[PDB]
Image (cartoon, rainbow, N blue to C red):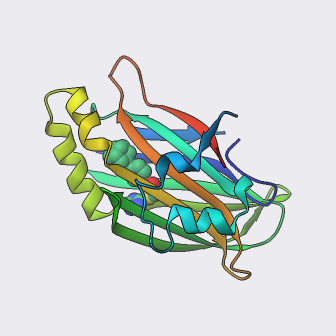
Amino acid sequence: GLGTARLQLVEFSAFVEPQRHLFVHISQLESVDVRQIYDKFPEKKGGLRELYDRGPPHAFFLVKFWADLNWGFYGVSSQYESLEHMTLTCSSKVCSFGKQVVEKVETERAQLEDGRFVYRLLRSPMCEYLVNFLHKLRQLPERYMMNSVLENFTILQVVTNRDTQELLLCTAYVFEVSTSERGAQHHIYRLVR
Ligand SMILES: O=C(CSc1nnc[nH]1)Nc1ccc([C@]23C[C@H]4C[C@H](C[C@H](C4)C2)C3)cc1
């Protein structure tokens, strides 16, 4: 369960269309030390270090993906939900070799549905950098080469209460490549210290 009392992730996927092909997908708990991965994110400000210091720790998660790169419109879809009416700020930092190369900030207001509030950020066009990176990563002859390249590639997703500036969720994404026989997969972890 990737979430807290105030906010949970319902679904998340990154895909390409001409049906959809999902490179990664979450639809709806072990632990990992944050110390392990200060290096793969920015550090001197707004880093994983600074954010985890502020807390709360229970809002910090790690997701390892094994992506399916064997298959247009390149999109990302995400959905959150909560019991409180809120307006969310969703920040996404793509990092290469610890350095931020993309920051994407989006806003989504609560939508009342079935006795709860949903937050649907759907078919958001995948940024030009990742589309370009993806088509290159595709070219590689071996999976072990893809994994070598990917071990210096991470994403940091921060979801804050726009109105109260409070952190609701912080997710760290790291990536490997799966085979065709073994579909896309994910393993969600809890960040601790
Ligand atoms: O994390 C987010 C939030 S959305 C966004 N921010 N900028 C653009 N889009 N999206 C996300 C996630 C994962 C992937 C990728 C990364 C590797 C592995 C696999 C195939 C491709 C290469 C693409 C999954 C792209 C995007």
Residue drawn at (83%, 67%) of the image: 84
Would you say 20 lies left or right of 152 here?
A: right
Q: Position of residue 172 (x, y in %)?
A: 52, 52
The reply to whether residue 98 is in sight is yes
Task: Residue at the far bottom: name it.
Answer: 163
Q: Position of residue 87 (x, y in %)?
A: 69, 75
**Residue 87, above or below 52:** below
Q: Position of residue 49 (x, y in %)?
A: 55, 63
State the quadrant of the N terminus: top right
Near-viewer residue (74 or 100): 100
Toward which corner of the image does residue 31 lie, by quadrant?
Answer: top right
**How many marks can you see?**
0
Residue drawn at (34%, 68%) of the image: 102
Near-viewer residue (73 or 22): 22
Would you say 83 lies left or right of 193 here?
A: right
The reply to whether residue 20 is in sight is no
Q: Position of residue 129 (x, y in %)?
A: 26, 61
Residue drawn at (52%, 34%) of the image: 186
